[PDB]
Amino acid sequence: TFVTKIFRSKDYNKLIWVFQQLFEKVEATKPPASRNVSAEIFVVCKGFKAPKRLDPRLLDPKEVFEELPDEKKVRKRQGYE
Amino acid sequence: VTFDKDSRLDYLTGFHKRKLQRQKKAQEFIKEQERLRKIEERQKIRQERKEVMEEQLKTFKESLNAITEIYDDSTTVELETLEPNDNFEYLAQLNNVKLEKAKFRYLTKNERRINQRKANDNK
RNA sequence: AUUCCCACUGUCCCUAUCUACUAUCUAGCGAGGCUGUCUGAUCAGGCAUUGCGUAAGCAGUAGAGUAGCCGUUACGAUCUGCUGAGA
Image (cartoon, rainbow over all chains, first blue to last red):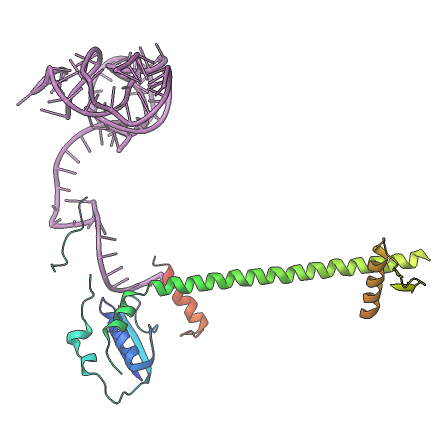
């Protein structure tokens, strides 16, 4: 069982997806000991699948955090194509 | 296991269709349960009315007290009786059928309540 | 109830301007356009706590459509000209 603490941010769902890929049940929580103002969340993962041939590209941060594809218009601060 | 882009896009891009699908399923389940409880309510009402009607009848009862014929010319005549009043058969069949039938929470509840109040009064 | 994502904002960087009300003294006493609505209609105006750049009029045979006949009465939004005019 893998128990970790994650700071909630825009890159929080990708970690959950990877954990679901490697674990049979993944679930997050916030124990009362952790202060409510803090953004930390404790996620546990039970039922390790233990693959015979794990994908090294699955645990590589270079592509785990791949960015999602996309009148006084909204300020263009998302870069260019 | 393998790392596939389609699964990660399906998981990340969603989070909203899944919630509305769950809401639709819950709503239709609630509607089905309501229709059920309604029909069993109908059952209870009909049974009450039938029982009171039978009791009324019972308590009023106490207060009460093809032939074919051949001729010599080889010609045959067919004679069948007819029933113009069909009520006799209906009452007889009613009498015949009547004869035939007869979750986990972290802390203590007190501590949980204090924590909830301390979180609530701040806002 | 709490935490993260996007969008917005005078909350702030960082204040500035306007309206209403208030405060002061004196006499006496004294602890151009639009919505709604109204002037019978245009024109021109009033009200709704600023409510939220081409005039009036005339003409055209051009003009969505309303209204006369099987070349043709009339009404007519809109558009064009007098008109960078009118105020």
